[PDB]
Length: 42
Image (cartoon, rainbow, N blue to C red; front, side):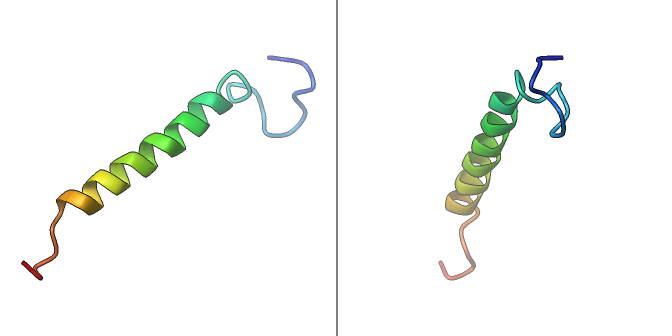
């Protein structure tokens, strides 16, 4: 869609922020889940 595009196919450069955001969101969810889901250690 963009231009330099090439590999890493579009729907991603305008969306790498989306991906990066998704990674960040996945990190946050993983982090929140990790911080929430208390271990049976108490």
